[PDB]
Length: 170
Image (cartoon, rainbow, N blue to C red):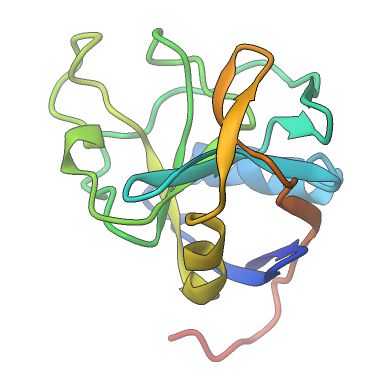
């Protein structure tokens, strides 16, 4: 279980270890190293998704490790409350940036291995704190650097904690 502790409250997340094993391992290594600590939701689009995991306040892009394989062909869908990996044009280019779907975004789902078919790999889902996600998705945005849709007031991920203990999210 992973918890993103934001300045607006906690987002509790369950990982799909069996269906996105290398994607989950990559994410939880970033979490454990403190990489998402003092980072922001830098791209917030109401009725679509909220995206973070790459930038400190003031839009300083954090250095990342080498990218991972795209595990999007795993049967998992970009439904409301899922987490998926952000990437650039090449399929195997995801590093640390991720996003929370705030509606079903079927057009993000794998449909094939052409550049245009690959889609975005789902690897986890919010199990508590969708109220916190719905607060974030509605905030005022503007341009910062080359980035569109950056909240005017920083939405800060203060820390992320990982637990492997028994839990009641069944």
